[PDB]
Amino acid sequence: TKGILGRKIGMTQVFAENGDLIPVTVIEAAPNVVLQKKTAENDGYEAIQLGFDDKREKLSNKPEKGHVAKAETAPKRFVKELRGVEMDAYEVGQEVKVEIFSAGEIVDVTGVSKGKGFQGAIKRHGQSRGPMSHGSRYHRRPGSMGPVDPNRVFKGKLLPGRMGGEQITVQNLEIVKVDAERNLLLIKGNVPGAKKSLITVKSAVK
Amino acid sequence: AVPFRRTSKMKKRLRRTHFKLNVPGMTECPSCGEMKLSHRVCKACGSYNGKDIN
Amino acid sequence: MIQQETRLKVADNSGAREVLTIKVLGGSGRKTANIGDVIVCTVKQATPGGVVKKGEVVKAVIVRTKSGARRSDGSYISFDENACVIIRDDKSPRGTRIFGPVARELRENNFMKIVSLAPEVI
Amino acid sequence: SYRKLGRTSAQRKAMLRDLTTDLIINERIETTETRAKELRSVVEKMITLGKRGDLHARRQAAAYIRNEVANEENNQDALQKLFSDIATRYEERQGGYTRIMKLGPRRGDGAPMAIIELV
Amino acid sequence: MQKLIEDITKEQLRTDLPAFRPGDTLRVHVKVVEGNRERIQIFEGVVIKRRGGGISETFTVRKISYGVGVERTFPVHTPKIAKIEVVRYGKVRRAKLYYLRELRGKAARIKEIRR
RNA sequence: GGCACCUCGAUGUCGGCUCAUCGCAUCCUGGGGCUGUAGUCGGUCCCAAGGGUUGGGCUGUUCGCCCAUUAAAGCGGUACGCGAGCUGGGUUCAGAACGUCGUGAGACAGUUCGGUCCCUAUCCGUCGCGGGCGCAGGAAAUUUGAGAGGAGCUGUCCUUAGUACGAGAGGACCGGGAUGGACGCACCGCUGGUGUACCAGUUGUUCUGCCAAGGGCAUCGCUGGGUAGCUAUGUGCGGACGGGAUAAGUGCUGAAAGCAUCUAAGCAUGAAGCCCCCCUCAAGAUGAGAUUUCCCAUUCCGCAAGGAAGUAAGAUCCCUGAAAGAUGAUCAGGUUGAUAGGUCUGAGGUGGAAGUGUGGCGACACAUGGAGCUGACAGAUACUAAUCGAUCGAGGACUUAACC
């Protein structure tokens, strides 16, 4: 398989030479560098781990600097790895850029979600709330615990808690335009995560 | 909404094991002599970042 | 979004004036009707002389709503009121002459007959 | 965003207006930390306003700051004292006319005091 | 961000548009294709709104048709708005002229500023 | 229903709302056998619990009956689930009445009108979030996956094809294609909603000595809009293709028992079912895993059992913050720096500021001028604040292989 890692800059709409209107997700991705080529006979499996954008020497520490000095680049802030790629396709230290994708290709997209915080059950899992009138003192409560005979509540009754911050994958997205000059991506749809955040883009396994 | 049993001594201490309060952060004043917080102006010397404040 | 029990204005010569959606068809529980789909309904008030009287269950399609209708180009169509036309099951209207502007969505929903008898199509 | 300061908008706006008038009054404020942090920006846009120093500016700053006495022997009101003296003093530094000095908290409630002075 | 957005959409935003205020009256030509038979339906009306920016800029227009008022909306820079021209210059006060839906019949006067 | 076994030093009783969960004696969807199964439809029976299993009218009603849809409108268990979650319509108080019974006070699983539902969560349990310690040095990252979760639902239309079948009527199996309903996930460009330090108009009163221009209060005084953020009714996507082992079933070969026989030996096929494939968590997995990179094995003491005291890598305290946030935590930053607030330039929004001058008795309208103003938005800018500091944090036991 094939895939890159970038930073989500924004999202807008773009016309596609037919009259219909196509909202798009805008992702800038400076050319990534493979730092380590994970191989089967020592790592138990094959993979490539690669870094996305630079860091200043102030925030760079000595261990990661020594790790990067094999591929002889600037230190990388954002490092992830992919599985299922062609093992001999990528030499260590080479770039991947943006042009390995072409417009019209179905795409698996994965990113962290927008963090929201401690929300109630109403927001968290969207089950309805009680009456707002006719004497109801049950305005926004999260429902009954469960039966009596098991003498305890079961695991996984869905309760108020924190939202967000947990990575989510949208499948079968379609890349509508690639701008290799500015190192930009432009995918139809809506991509999860806050602005200027992590976003990784993969070829769809479907 | 009622304690069904009394809480024993070791349970009480075990709850209170985190209720201890931390020390502040001191730093030696720019003007000599005494102790001061970080990012607070000096109470005694009346100075901060080497500069004097009335 | 035409919804269950919404009162509708009629825009043809079938004699019905105000109809009352029984509920919408399609899936098992359809909470909504947008432009184009058949809704079963009863008639609340009517002209004296008409093919349909007051108070019988009939089948109809809404032809113009006040909530917007979205076309693929990016345009939207919307109106000031809600109207529908009574359709018998031959998928063509009961009245012989309809009034007012009608949306284009009833083209690709196969409705050339009412589209032709429409006085104006936007 | 911007802080709420534990009060709704009416007396909040009255509070900030009163503090910034006090700032122009005596060029040095002792208050709590968060009042100082939200104080800084507003007094320094009034300082930009006074640096602009035209008649639209006079009326705009009149609509926010209040009329105290600032130099009583000259009967100098706060508006004119701003618009004459302080704009001419700080016309050159294109921003950042405020400083925050933090102190130990009060005996009464441990509220973190700050020193605000215009410099 | 908005720098990169406008550079990526400059090639697609249209240019041949007379500048208009949302209290004026227009006719707009659309190239709607019905049965692979391309033809132009003209749409005469009055702007009610002009909202957005970049190519997210959009505007909308009202017309009274057979006693029924209609909203028509478009994005500003679609390829498939063929021709647009101003017929008459309006004088309004509001930026958004929303009350025209309530105001039906003559009492919806738009004054000719002749500017 | 019978018995009276725990509870009368209190175990809250119908129905409804919110929330589920389990069984299968399966309502639909899946696979089959028989048919008095031609085909479209069915009847029964078997395998199958993965998922789903509608809105109204009436009555307190479960239940029913009716209206309209749907593939279907399942049956039951969980103190007739669920009141320290909610409801109080009815039964189950005290008032009052009707019918009836009683000489009467009064009474009726007879009716009718009205009728106080307490609790600051201790421990289990549940949902999130932190600190310590461990993982025979000390750190920064990347991971493996045991093992957990979730999704796992369906219609309609076109074609095959008016083709097989059928005197006819009518109408397919299998296979392709398009599109939808409901759910869930994500997110503001669009449609909008909100938007209480944004803008504009406007009444009363009061205040800034007066006019002008403004301030306060009147639900944000009212009204029309509206940035960011949040958001659905708005937008994008999913439940695809597959593999393996199967259930009911269909078999191939073949004796026991010269035949027969899906059977005992062997070899197959066969489900929305099981395990994977999809998504997420996951080494406290004490079995504490793996990879790469950095720090090195200093100073003293009993010399040695082992301690203590400075440190390296690297962290922390403290400070500026938000894309994160109840606080912790996370992340961006801390003077070789764009972290936040200013300033300037913008986007966008409100929309024609004041002051002038003209016309007009006048309220007013014009030009100056897309002017004036602008919370969160995005670029630059060292202007102001992230200063001096401090604290923590390595020196490593037996054997087999192997070579100083």
Image: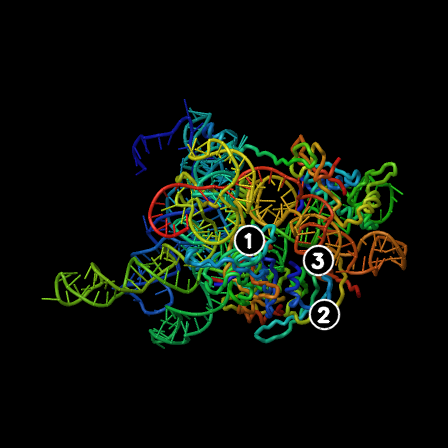
Q: Quadrant of residue F265?
A: bottom left
Residue at disc 1, secondary structure: helix
Residue D22's spot in the image, x, y percent? 77, 39
* Residue sitting nearer the eye, D8 or F11: D8
Q: Earlier in the sequence, mark 2 or mark 3?
A: 2
Residue at the disc numbered 2: E85
Describe the colour scheme in one phrase: rainbow
- Judging depth in this view, the residue of F251 and D5 nearest the camera is D5
- Judged left or right of residue F158, residue E55 is right
Q: Position of residue A43 (x, y in %)?
A: 43, 55
Q: Is residue D19 left or right of residue C101?
A: right
Q: Residues within 10 Å of mark 1 (few under 14, many from 20)?
A: some
Q: Which mark is residue A65?
A: 1
Q: Chain of mark 1?
A: A
Please report the residue visible at 52 percent of the width from the left and 66 percent of the height from the top. A105
- Which disc, if any, is residue E41? none
Q: Secondary structure at mark 2?
A: strand
Q: Are marks 1 and 2 on the same chain?
A: no
In the rendering, at what x and y percent does residue F235 appear? 57, 60
Please give the name of the residue rendered at 81% of the width and 46% of the height, measured from the top-left corner: D87
Amino acid found under the numbered disc labelled 3:
Lys
Residues at marks 2 and 3, common chain? yes
What residue would you read off at disc 3?
A: E96
Mark 1–mark 2 Cα distance, whole angstroms, equals: 63 Å
Q: Secondary structure at mark 3?
A: loop
